[PDB]
Length: 116
Ligand SMILES: COc1cc2c(cc1-c1c(C)noc1C)ncc1[nH]c(=O)n([C@H](C)c3ccccn3)c12
Image 1 (spheres, rainbow, N blue to C red):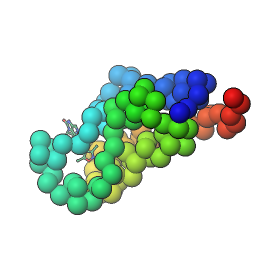
Image 2 (cartoon, helix red, strand yellow):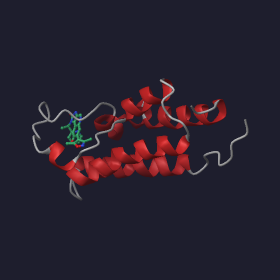
Image 3 (tube, protein in one colour):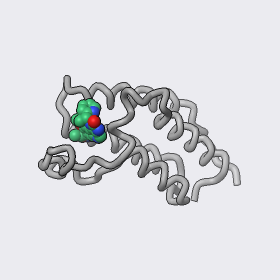
Image 4 (cartoon, rainbow, N blue to C red):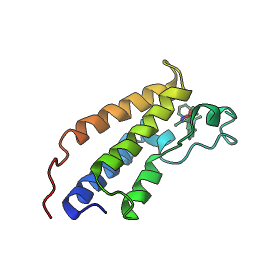
C-alpha cells in the first residue's frame, strides 16, 4: 500500500476537492449517486463503476490504494461517470468540469518517483 509522502499528497488533493470552499459545485460529488432519491432510474444503464469523492477518501484512509495512479483512476471515474450520464450544458456537467480542472491542476504536482 501507498507510502507516507504519496499518501499525504493524495489526502491533500482529496481534502481540497471536498472542501467547503468549493461547496457550490462539489456537493453532487461528495456522496454516491442515489438514483432512487434523485429520480434518474437509468443511471446504472450508463454508469457501471460508480464513484464519489467520499468513497475515494475512505479507500485512501483504508490503505486500499497501492499507488497514486490507482487514486487518479478512481477520481477520474467520478467525472467520466458525470459526463456519461449528464449531457453537455447541464448544471452537474458544468460542476464536474469545474472540479475536474481543479483536480488536474493539483494533480499536476504529484510525486513521480518512489524511494523506499
Ligand atoms: C443532477 O445531478 C445530480 C444532482 C445531485 C446529486 C448528484 C447528481 C448526479 C451526479 C454527480 N451524477 O449524476 C447525477 C444525476 N447529488 C446530490 C444532490 N443534491 C442535490 O440537491 N442535487 C440537485 C438535484 C442538483 C441538481 C443540479 C446540480 C446540482 N445539484 C444533487
